[PDB]
Image 1 (cartoon, rainbow, N blue to C red):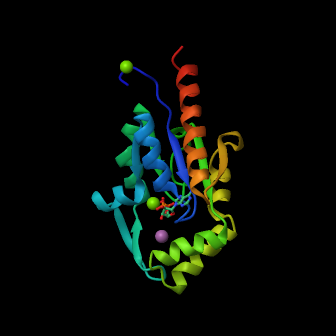
Image 2 (cartoon, helix red, strand yellow):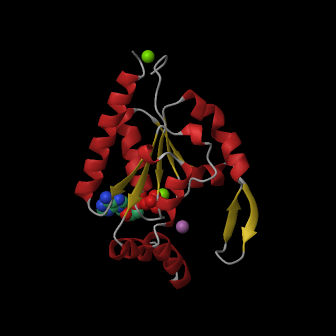
Image 3 (cartoon, protein in one colour):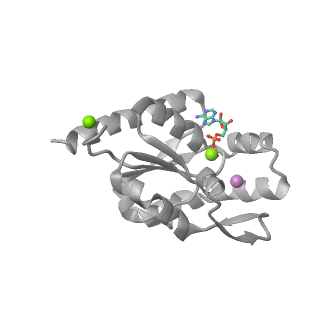
Length: 175
Ligand SMILES: Nc1ncnc2c1ncn2[C@@H]1O[C@H](COP(=O)(O)OP(=O)(O)O)[C@@H](O)[C@H]1O
Ligand SMILES: [Li+]
Ligand SMILES: [Mg+2]
Ligand SMILES: [Mg+2]
């Protein structure tokens, strides 16, 4: 992988849509580095403030950017986070917003043990297409794509289509 130009990919969308499942499988099958922003924030304790209503530490956005910037500059990173408005626009060559039918997403999040308030917040987030709109506001239209993420066959199609995009991008950028 040394001395190859490699792309960076954002996987975004409501909690429960399948970002981590897709990201880890993509990294295994491409050799690109997988980064879970929530896990990274946990491991490196990148928090500032506590959110009273949602009951969780608040992500320190500047510190996350500082933590990751050098790696992103070097390329070949798949980043997984529900949001995207604070990332430098230059980081990503393509952005995928995974989408899940509300009925399907609810069962996933219920299985996680989310309580009523948290289930409702996330379910509304998806039905209002909040994170899709956040992606389109933050990145060029042409590099933002919605991916269906309801069934295992769709996960496989998503993996296949992205692996193929990665191969073409690498060819196009290592003439
Ligand atoms: N395309 C899919 N089809 C069926 N189940 C899926 C799909 N993608 C993810 N899942 C399942 O949905 C749950 C949430 O996926 P996860 O990758 O943790 O979501 P996120 O990281 O977006 O919160 C997991 O149980 C996972 O196995
Ligand atoms: Li969550
Ligand atoms: Mg090489
Ligand atoms: Mg996840």
